[PDB]
Length: 281
Image (cartoon, rainbow, N blue to C red; front, side):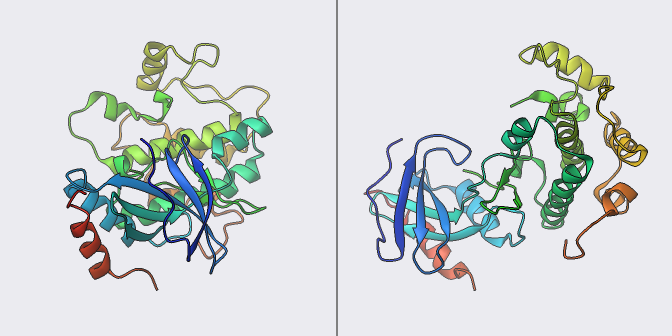
């Protein structure tokens, strides 16, 4: 729905109003102090400001890892609460794959290492699964792109692990491993696994393949035995048997060329603003 007029024109330069994408209906602006490009999501003051929004905002604000799309600040308008966050201006990872046809094994590993670091961090903060848009990770503006995961944002069924389709109870972290595997596969192969590429809207078939873990790396795609093995260890239907993030962190494919590395807004101010934004002019 339509966005309120520009505000805070003394810290922010308005870059563009965008009405669709991963950041949805949002507002691109520039911080005049940092030179940083940020995105702003808007929620109408009033009832819409509820305990889920409260919990998402708090949780978002808590996350400080360079591969997570980070929370900047919350701002009050007379009609909306403004939530300012980092903007990934590099587009979707998927678009880069398509442009390249497929990635080399080394470029895939470069991104996959960032993916797993970000996911490992989220998991230790108890942010699993539904809190992460792992099916549509993004890239920053950098010439050498950094991976960016929207957590708490405000596709292909391939990303859905078999247990998520069949079982009543499941561990979300383990389902995340499956999803990472799918992202790895697509980077290497240039197409999703399980999904029939000439029939991508055939969800029945896709699901059948997911359940039976039926995938096949094309003959012309050549990957190391290490890489092939890691994939076979992620694409395991029984979640109890699936390789875990820690085990992935210790896998030899993952360790190759691994970079050793892998003053906000006060909680008082944020809670006070969320509170005030419950009253709806």
